[PDB]
Length: 276
Ligand SMILES: CN(CCOc1ccc(C[C@H](Nc2ccccc2C(=O)c2ccccc2)C(=O)O)cc1)c1ccccn1
Ligand SMILES: [Cl-]
Image 1 (cartoon, helix red, strand yellow):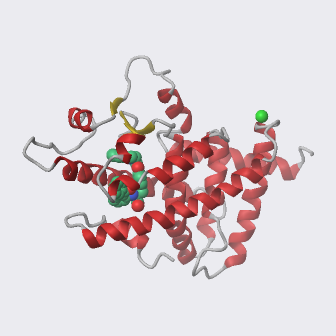
Image 2 (cartoon, rainbow, N blue to C red):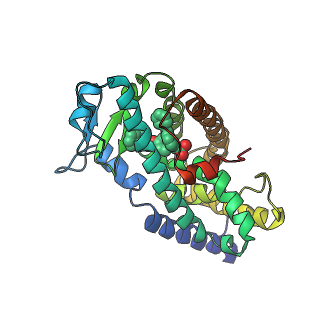
Image 3 (cartoon, rainbow, N blue to C red):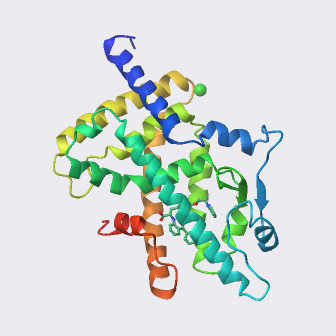
């Protein structure tokens, strides 16, 4: 391998994406792991590990109050539902801002830009959610709370099924030990998929993804020298991301049919509309 104009341009591309990733996503993997491993000495997340602690964390986590004369299981489900919805809407905006910085993206046909974001955002959301997870739980509300996996799993059906595929993915994904510099290129690779349904100009997207893939391959070689076949293993993880989306869509459809007063935010409806 040589540090020639080709590879140097790949490094400059990796740096450009890292810088735009830092600008677009306030809570990076580096900051989240610091919090999760207790490196933040003064301010620490409140832990939500059961019903009692969820209701004691209402103020810190922006949850509507739950009085003692309500169906506790139902109201908690609503709070978690609204909480995830708020976060997803914010996350779409961060990813959209990020995508505009991907070299070549803004030059694509505007309809193809929208199609790529439509099919990409949720896969990126689940990838970056893993940065905020360990086997115990997930950081929420800008890292001010930590909600446990078993608590999310105990919610009344169908709500208690929602997060488990995300945690199972995160544990395997986090064992790859990627850092923010790796992730910035990987999420660009997710976006620039030439196989999204309804793309008009496939060739310009593939040429960009080919370049991103080259950048990711070089990044992993330089940053993880003794991690054998890390590139291959990371690409296989895209298989799991797509299944997360598939199951999540199905669970949301159960909610649309068998639940009241939990309609999706309009932006999320537009993303899910005619998706696959
Ligand atoms: C666990 N979590 C971290 C963020 O988790 C996410 C988990 C999933 C998502 C994606 C997002 N999900 C929803 C969007 C709208 C309404 C509900 C959901 C749920 O996902 C949901 C549904 C039923 C029961 C529970 C959740 C999407 O599809 O756009 C985005 C974020 C929380 C929890 C409470 C408050 C804030 N943070
Ligand atoms: Cl290594």
